[PDB]
Image (spheres, coloured by chain):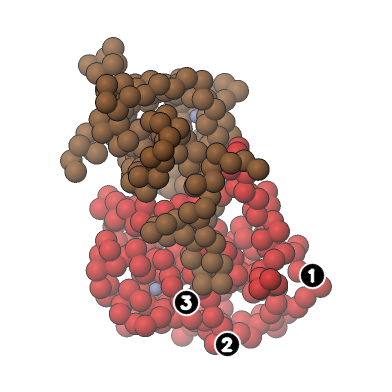
Chain colours: A red, B brown
């Protein structure tokens, strides 16, 4: 009854337990344990840097986001920018990664203008990061955040960057992000700006 | 419809509104296979193939051991074999691989195990092809770790598999034989010991 606006998305998800397949349109998926992600994160951190690990989860996310936007692209042409864009935040729910809640969204392809402010609720990433690390000193939601930047950047034809303003990892009640075109912040590893920003805004 | 998997599908809930996916206690993620391809490409070039391969078995092993924990006391009114099938079934629910049983005999009590399965539509195989193309040797490492991790735990001893044909080598499907450790004609902390073992291919 109540995934009225999700439904068109669910309609592309095919479970096929009997053949070891799960599909979103043309692409496969895997139902994965979060605590297994928690291990992959700590093991990576142990092998590489905080920095190289960080960088991986973000680039990862950027990818997932771009692919979902490819997918959900030819999918709501009846609708407008805002309602189509939403597919993104909805997919993050669908994949059980995070609950997106919109404080503010203003966008327009042709104006090359974007500003998003959302609350992330129930982030897995923050939850797993606490087990393996405890109270962090920076935000933890790298993957979610890469995906955020990715999805968005696909949708507008320009690079959209997010800052995680508050994070459950850091003790904040919910997590929160803000997203604006790269330049409105005063070779496509956009991965490096994200880290440089959370740095050069102490 | 397909009633062999129900006691599993049941323990799964999709709360898309609050962005949680649920397996009993455990919380789950529906993910692109891209994160695993990427990880494969990055690791391949930062560390050896040996190192990348090992890491992947280790990861596969942790998930095998988890489902093993979770499905543990779930099928007490069936026998060892149908109980055990939980792992192979889970691997398919998780959309990683279809397991088609060629042969299976197990006794926890007698310390006995022999599994010979076919793997079909292996996701790992797929990933390796579109990152590295034809392998020299079987490539379904994550999958193999799981096999090893799951079996091992149920059995309460060290069960090691070998991929014997792999889509990654042009075979039509992949194949695997799992025996106990001592039944191989070649010779905690121990979770790392075991990954070290299933790495001698
Ligand atoms: Zn967070
Ligand atoms: Zn294979």
Percent from the top left, x then y, of residue A58?
A: 44, 62
The alpha-carbon separation of the residues under discs 1 and 2 comes to 22 Å
Labels 2 and 3 share a subunit: yes
The answer for which chain carries disc 3 is: A
Count residues near mark 3 (Cα–Cα under 10 Å), then give few for <14, some for 14-19, many for 20+.
many
Count residues near mark 1 (Cα–Cα under 10 Å), then give few for <14, some for 14-19, many for 20+.
few
Quarter of the picture holding the C terminus of chain B: top left
Who's the residue at 28% across and 16% down the image? B183
Who's the residue at 69% across and 79% down the image? A82
Image mark for residue A104: 2
Q: Secondary structure at mark 1?
A: loop
Left or right: A15 in relation to A43: right
The quarter of the picture showing ligand 1? bottom left
Q: For mark 3, what is the residue?
A: A120
Q: Secondary structure at mark 2?
A: strand
Task: Kindly tell me whether mark 3's CB lies below 8 Å from ligand 1.
Answer: yes
Quarter of the picture holding the N terminus of chain B: top right
The alpha-carbon separation of the residues under discs 2 and 3 comes to 13 Å
Image mark for residue A77: 1
The answer for which chain carries disc 1 is: A
Q: Quadrant of residue A105?
A: bottom right
């Amino acid at each position: 009854e109540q995934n009225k606006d999700i439904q068109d998305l669910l309609d592309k998800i095919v479970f096929d337990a009997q053949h070891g397949q799960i599909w979103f349109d043309e692409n496969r998926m895997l139902l994965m344990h979060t605590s297994i992600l928690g291990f992959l994160r700590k093991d990576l951190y142990q092998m590489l840097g905080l920095e190289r690990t960080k960088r991986f989860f973000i680039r990862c996310g950027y990818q997932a986001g771009m692919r979902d936007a490819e997918v959900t692209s030819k999918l709501r042409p009846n609708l407008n920018e805002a309602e189509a864009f939403m597919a993104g935040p909805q997919m993050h729910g669908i994949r059980g990664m995070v609950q997106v809640e919109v404080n503010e969204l203003h966008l327009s392809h042709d104006l090359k203008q974007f500003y998003a402010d959302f609350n992330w609720l129930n982030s897995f990433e923050a939850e797993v990061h606490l087990s393996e690390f405890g109270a962090s000193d920076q935000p933890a939601c790298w993957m979610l955040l890469g995906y955020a930047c990715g999805y968005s950047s696909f949708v507008m034809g320009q690079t959209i960057i997010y800052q995680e303003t508050h994070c459950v990892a850091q003790g904040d009640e919910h997590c929160r992000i803000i997203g604006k075109p790269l330049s409105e912040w005063e070779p496509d590893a956009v991965s490096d700006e994200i880290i440089a920003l959370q740095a050069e805004l102490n």
